[PDB]
Length: 134
Length: 104
Length: 87
Ligand SMILES: O=C(NCc1ccc(Cl)cc1)[C@@H]1C[C@@H](O)CN1C(=O)c1ccccc1Cl
Image (spheres, rainbow over the protein chains, first blue to last red):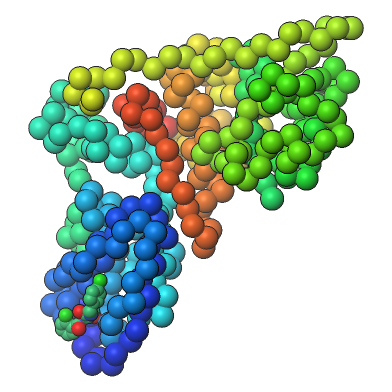
């Protein structure tokens, strides 16, 4: 539904991780399925072989936090500048807490039921790919 | 080039930006607009060292590398009680609790 | 132009109205030049004010955005404040 166009037209891309995170590049195949690629260390660049009309998205390789590419969510091939978005203070706080607490132990933190469910609702690529149908 | 500050006196903290080239006296005029106190009744400090009016904020140590949005630099403020200046006093913020065992 | 945000312990935080309006809760509460937070401590409200300046500076930038730092000790309380403030 939100897939890559099978152009067969080679396009040279340079993925630049202009973020403090380890980036996981995700290619959406011809069937809309997300295909992960080898991870980019914090301030690193990589010359990659892609194709015109192919769809890409970049997430944090560990936590799956969403990243921007050339100030937007999706990249269509060329420079792919992967940056942190200005996350909300809530999302940023959830990120830090998730990074300090084991999923099982989230119910042991003295906070409201809504916040437990906010921590449990981890970032996901499939969930993101569904929000992008509207 | 902007610089990000916390202007602090007692339990009062002003959050403002200024140019590296802005002078100490120009910052005093900013405080004046907010706290309704004239530069002559003001004294500004960096780490409890009194800053000269004519010196720029860069010369005073507030730079892009030191005074960031997410981590602003602290400028100390003191008022005059006609005459004599009050001693610099910055009330420390509230203390956070002991880290939960579950987040250690 | 500016607004006063008073914490649970009387610390008064003077911030630009544009910045304080980042919080939907504050935006609502401001319709008065002062807002009292009977629940948020100073160590929490100061980092919120920092978030406001960080958000206004980095929103729609094209450069490189730095990570917003959060100490482990504040993480839990800041989460509750951010959740309350629609931040
Ligand atoms: O694999 C590919 N390039 C090599 C590469 C190695 C490491 C990294 Cl980090 C990035 C890129 C390309 C990219 C995407 O269009 C996919 N693709 C294809 O060559 C392709 C084309 C048609 C069907 C299936 C595939 Cl895998």
